Image (cartoon, rainbow, N blue to C red; front, side):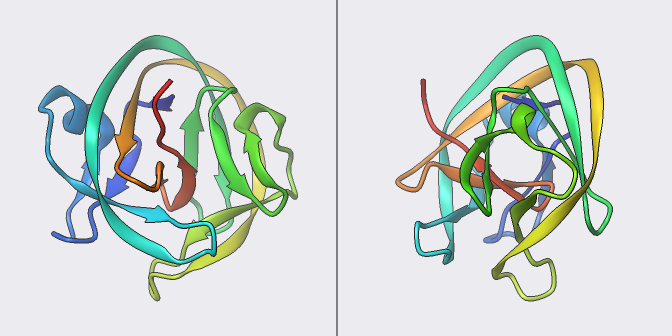
Length: 142
């Protein structure tokens, strides 16, 4: 799951939302989702999850964004899907390029120790992924 404060861009409206506001208000936003060939597409959120307070780790990405997620949350990388907690400085994660809107890869500059945060998840229709702080992450249903 993803930490409070995680920014989620809605490509249909152009609005960026904090994930806790999306969940707390059951907001019918779209997200940017990735398909298996690396193309990006707008897809609606269909479920909203409040996952409680948990440890989250931080992945600071080239460009300056920091993704805060539980160590078990899956991130799309140069290797395929990997748990956030298994990633190291120098690994490359899939990102949405903020100027072009297409998928590229960016290097992890730093891994940050845990902090306690409220956490959340979203289920995204069809593609089961979303862009969070610019990074392609899993958005499935357990």
